[PDB]
Length: 83
Ligand SMILES: Nc1ncnc2c1ncn2[C@@H]1O[C@H](COP(=O)(O)O)[C@@H](O)[C@H]1O[C@H]1O[C@H](COP(=O)(O)O)[C@@H](O)[C@H]1O
Image (tube, rainbow, N blue to C red):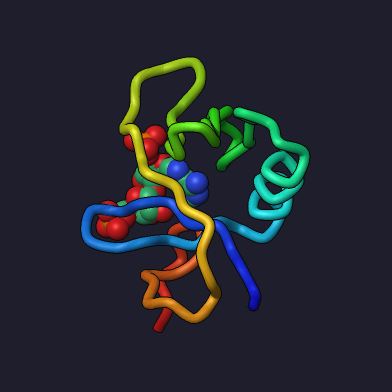
């Protein structure tokens, strides 16, 4: 039973990078309703009640997030395609 964090792409799921995934897991484990993440130098909000992420300070997409097993189909990790 091993788990990872994922964010929605247009037609699939991407796994979060290792550091961010650990931060999400910490926040989830403490019962936090939300947390902030640094993604490529930009601040994002992870809303753990509604299970969505979005950029903190400027416009962007709302992406679904989920916590699921490692052994699911996925597109890659943090924008780096699996080959
Ligand atoms: N948690 C994250 N980790 C890495 N990159 C991210 C993340 N959140 C946003 N970005 C990137 O930040 C940009 C703006 O996202 P927005 O509007 O939400 O703030 C996007 O390019 C985001 O990257 C995604 O989309 C790419 C295409 O994936 P397809 O739809 O073809 O599956 C792919 O690189 C994928 O990683």
